[PDB]
Image: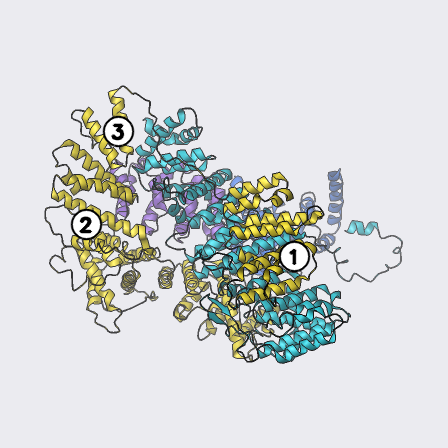
Amino acid sequence: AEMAPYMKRLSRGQTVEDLLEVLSDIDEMSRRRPEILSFFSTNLQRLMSSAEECCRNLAFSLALRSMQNSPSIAAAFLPTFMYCLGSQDFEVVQTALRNLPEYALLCQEHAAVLLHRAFLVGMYGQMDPSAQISEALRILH
Amino acid sequence: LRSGNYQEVIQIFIEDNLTLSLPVQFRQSVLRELFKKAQQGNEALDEICFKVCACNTVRDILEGRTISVQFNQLFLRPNKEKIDFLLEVCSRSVNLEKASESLKGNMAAFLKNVCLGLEDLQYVFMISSHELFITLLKDEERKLLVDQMRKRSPRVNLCIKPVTSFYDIPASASVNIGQLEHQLILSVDPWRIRQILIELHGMTSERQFWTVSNKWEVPSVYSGVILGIKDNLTRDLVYILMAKGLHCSTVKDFSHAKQLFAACLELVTEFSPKLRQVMLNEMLLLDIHTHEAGTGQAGERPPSDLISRVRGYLEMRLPDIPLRQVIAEECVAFMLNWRENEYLTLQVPAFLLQSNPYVKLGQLLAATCKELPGPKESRRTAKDLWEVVVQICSVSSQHKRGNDGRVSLIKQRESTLGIMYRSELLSFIKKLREPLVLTIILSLFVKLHNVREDIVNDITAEHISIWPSSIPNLQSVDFEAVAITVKELVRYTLSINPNNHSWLIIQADIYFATNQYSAALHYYLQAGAVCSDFFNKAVPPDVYTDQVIKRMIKCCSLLNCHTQVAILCQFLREIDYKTAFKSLQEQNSHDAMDSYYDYIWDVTILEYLTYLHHKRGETDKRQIAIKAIGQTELNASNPEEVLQLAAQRRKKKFLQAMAKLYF
Amino acid sequence: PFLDALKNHVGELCGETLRLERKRFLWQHQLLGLLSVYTRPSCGPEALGHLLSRARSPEELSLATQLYAGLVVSLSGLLPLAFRSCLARVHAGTLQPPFTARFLRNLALLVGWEQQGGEGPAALGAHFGESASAHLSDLAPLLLHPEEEVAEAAASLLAICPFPSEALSPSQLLGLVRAGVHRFFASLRLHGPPGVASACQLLTRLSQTSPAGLKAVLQLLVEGALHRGNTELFGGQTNRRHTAAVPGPGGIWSVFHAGVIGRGLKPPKFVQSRNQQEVIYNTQSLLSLLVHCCSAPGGTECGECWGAPILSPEAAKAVAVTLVESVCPDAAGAELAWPPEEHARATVERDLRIGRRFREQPLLFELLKLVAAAPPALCYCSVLLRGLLAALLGHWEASRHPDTTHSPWHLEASCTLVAVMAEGSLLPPALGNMHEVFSQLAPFEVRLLLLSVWGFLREHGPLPQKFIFQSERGRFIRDFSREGGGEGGPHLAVLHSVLHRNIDRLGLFSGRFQAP
Amino acid sequence: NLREVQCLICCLLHQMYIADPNIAKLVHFQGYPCELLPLTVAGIPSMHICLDFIPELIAQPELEKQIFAIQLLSHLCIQYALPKSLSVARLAVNVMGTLLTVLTQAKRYAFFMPTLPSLVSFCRAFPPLYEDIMSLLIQIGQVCASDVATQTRDIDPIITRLQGSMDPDVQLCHCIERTVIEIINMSVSGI
């Protein structure tokens, strides 16, 4: 009941103003009592592929913190992370590689396909992801 | 052929099919003369032309040579007589009692691929009912062919009516309540809904049946006025029908929403005229959205009576009705969308023009729209549009009494010295579809992004630059807000016409300014592929300007692709040899070296390549450069036409290769 | 509690929904409906996706449609989110390939069911076409899938899926062109002429887009056909054993040899083997696809039929340009006006290269006939015709045989070449009917005839102009009355001297060369 | 029975190599088929002194000698993990990068096709080379990708970002992606 109006705002959101303001509110009230992010999974999936850079960064950070609370849900955000890694917006892929090693540790069962797609996106598409994937490799052992 | 008895020629060709007597090249020559003298003026020859073409192709398929392109041309539009004559000729052509097995195999394969060539099913039917087709193929392959032909467009049957797990004669009050509720939720037909409501109020005593589906939503002012009817049946009926109509308009079911709002119209007539005017505003919403969605961009015009009723709605002015602003949104959007440049200054009086900021912004935008076809300045309209848009992007408090950051324009969403908030500005420009006003707003926001936000050197491209240069109170406008709104406006304007080269150039420049070189190169290549037909013709110099090509060179250089830099800097009006030599001197290229040496046509750059490969130890790339120089196509002293045509061939192939890699 | 326990049990709930029991399926269907109405995110796109990823029969598609119809009265934006979830599951490591092949098949059946009828599809405001067209860039790479069933389902879907009314972005337009040509060639290799209907439909559907798409389709289609990996369809192209066998000639005496010239024997040489039925019918399939692509819009259904639809003179120009690009990329003789005869002795390397290209791949000749039936087009192939003619001139200069049937291919190439240039309204009908004597002449005699052809093209060039666009039945026509030469005076004189020499054998065919 | 002959021959070769290292240097300059490279390295201890001339063998103008040196060094680094082996491995990575700068396309295929499993061996032997190895891969990947865009292809691998006798370039791209797969699955299961 305490989370219904915020998520009603998140679901019925059109402008960048409303989404950014609700994301700021939920980040502020998720700094303490961080177990409330389990309800914000599907909407965080949908907003993680949004084109605006600030709201996308907030959604990515919230998703990583939601992994940090309970890593058993990392198998559920995999299709969205794979879509962000292989989309045609050229900013979702860079924000995906910026958050690539943390999610690579936090998944640990499907890291092979993730890093495989990272190599093909950075290989066929002209960009350099080598540092991030190699750092994920060194801290993955 | 000398006389004109062409049918006699047709039976000669059938006899030649039976006997294989006449030379094949003679038959092709006769086909040539028949086609040509059909093109000389007689329209009665096309029948004979098809007949002789069928005879020639059946001769070719008996003797196992190719199928002519004329035969494929005459079955672009098949017909009953054509396939009937083809089957008749194929039946007369082969004598089954004395034919070799190769001949039967050839005829069966020809019939099979003619069946595959057909698209409409009854032609496949009567070509599969001929005795020749049944005799020449054993039945399993015939059934296989028929099966794969009916698989193309299956007559699938799907049921649309929803699940009703209902048992007859419930004999219970609460169960029957549930049945009529589930039927009420599912029903879309308003007369059926009326039946459910009257029976439901008849059997129950004093239960209000609007709080029975929480997904139904009514606007706040309309919910305030709609709960004022005294009778319970009318409250429940008008509430749930108008909620269902609004939801059907939301989910793009326009005809059902039209019927629902029509039932609402015929029943609200008794109670009040205020609710009547409200729901005629709803009718205007439905008609505007139906015209803008059904006809779309392919619609011819508005039907000129909807124009009258929106024209009226902008001048109703009855102060006792609730008015949602989205009606005026669609009114101004429709008024600007279909290019009516007459409701700007002669009509639409100031007598509450300034109350609705939407009307004022649309008026100012249409005022700037009419200015452009004047080779003349008259730029009061562009001036005030510039002022209202720099004021909408301005923060109110100078030293930020509330919170010290200016970035709060995207956070606080208050404190704007404008007639409207920026989010409603994006909502307004996202409802415009006309290209001229959209590119006006795009040039405006490009110019507002190009005012040296702190320091910026790379100016984004702009199709027209007529706006005032000096900005008063530059500290007022929040510039990260300008970047956010120009990214919104560009990515939206790509969703109005993706094949517009100027918008693609603008997107590429914005990606280049934000140090996204790969995306900038992608959109530059994309603009080149829009303006020239995937580089089949030369790209005009008004798209790939020297600035554009220089930006592409910079993008290739910062991605460590240096042979591409050399090739791409051959493109300029004056060849930039300095950046070519500096790029080719480096040793960390992430693009190919030798296989890009085919797209070079300047002897000077190949000279430098040979010198670099001789100094640095490349004994094999040097030979590639020598082979490139030694071509008799890239000599310096050729005629100018040969050199420029080789240059444009290499330009086409290189730009296609870049469109192969990116894009 | 019941609703949010089924929130995470919806997978098994829908999995046992598809069984179609006696009365259980209605109960679990309403259970799914109330679930997806209740739950705050939605849980309707996932239910629709699961009903679409596992439907293998028409009635369970029907249950999917009842689910969407029961859900559309309350929720909104269901099908786009469902397709996002499905395609994201496809492109990730999950949704194992039978499931995605089945899902693409069900989507193809649904979007085909929309574009029919009107009693049923118009009742449910589903808009499968627009939702499927929104994800077209996400859907094109599935034509490149390693599993054949996934690629076939994607081909059927892209063949039936409508394009956006927004038109199509050039990047995803080009990507669709690549997917279409590769799927056409791969399905041509694997299945054959039965099984390319989806790829041909997709290519001919996005060929009728903006003309840049048409040039892209034609170019990639007929340069992929001449690639090494696809030209086979259309015509074609130690020490221990050393020391075990070194007895006798060695010993305390030197070995017999002095070395090895290269690496030894040059292989055992490969013998190519084909069957002509597959060759001719893959050629038939490709030329059918091209003649669909190069045709005009049409769609009038006027008259009593029996007629020839026009082939566009612009599409055939694109085919001609990319054919010239594929065969000879050089630009030495790129002018469309023929040079003098002695100039043929200069660029003999290029002439031999075009001769080799026409000899290796027969499809080139076939493509010329495609260029033939659009009379402004073969004028752009003047370089190709000139080079092949010069190669034939060289062969008939070097020929010493008494009769021309001793060299089959060169005789066939000469007769086919002059027949194609007679198709393209380059030569007069009087002079273009000479090839039927080529089978029974001497090599110098056919050489003199081809020099007469070369001289006529000197005097009356193969320019893109000098065709009049006659508009009542709009086509380009070259009428050989008004150039001032008409039938070539000296040329027909030389040809008639050729007939007048071999009266002994060219008796019956003398009636073809009579004056008009 | 094959293994008995193999180990007896390994014993004789170890005796002959410790008799005089010049024969070992001459033989490794001459070369033998790569399928013997495990057996010769695992079974002959004396191949440790083979790490003395890998800088000299990799500096020869002949190219197939450089592939043999790279492969032999990789198997040695699998066997003997020493600072000397890591230093010569870094030298090998630098040599491969330099030859990536200087190679014609056909010679680039002929050089980089048989090497790339050696990069898996190098990455398996030594963690501190990972990113360096990774850098080389991404570079070779995109340069091969650029070559794919140079001419038309029968498979079009650029749009295949989802998963016989072919074009050499698409074979090289496939080899690059498979050696990346092998590196990643080595890293995942490498504890």
The relative height of residue C110 versus residue C231 in the rendered view (above or below) is above
Q: Which of marks 1 and 3 is nearer the N terminus?
A: 1
Q: Is mark 3 on a helix, strand or loop?
A: helix
Q: Residues within 10 Å of mark 1 (few under 14, many from 20)?
A: some
Q: Chain C is drawn in which colour?
A: cyan
Q: Mark 3 points at which residue?
A: B181
Q: Residue at x 30, y 38 (%)?
A: C75
Q: Looking at the figure, which quarter contains the C terminus of chain B?
A: bottom left
**Amino acid bearing label 1:** Arg
| Residue B165 in view | yes
Going by the image, does C359 lie left or right of C403?
A: left
Q: Which of marks 1 and 2 is nearer the N terminus?
A: 1
The relative height of residue A131 versus residue B43 in the rendered view (above or below) is above
Q: Colour of chain D?
A: blue
**Relative image position of residue C495 (x, y in whole percent):** 67, 76
Viewer-closest of B115 and D38 = B115
Q: Please, which chain is the residue tagged with disc 2 on? A: B
User: In the orientation shown, which residue stands out farthest toward the top?
Assistant: B171
Q: Name the residue under label 2.
A: B325
Q: Is mark 1 on a helix, strand or loop?
A: loop
Q: Chain B is drawn in which colour?
A: yellow
Viewer-closest of C108 and D101 = C108
Q: State the CA–CA distance, disc 1 to disc 3.
A: 73 Å
**Amino acid bearing label 3:** Glu
Q: Mark 1 points at which residue?
A: B65
Q: Chain A is drawn in which colour?
A: purple
Going by the image, does C106 lie left or right of B490?
A: right
Q: Please, which chain is the residue tagged with disc 3 on? A: B
Q: Please, which chain is the residue tagged with disc 1 on? A: B
Q: Which mark is in front, 1 or 2?
A: 1
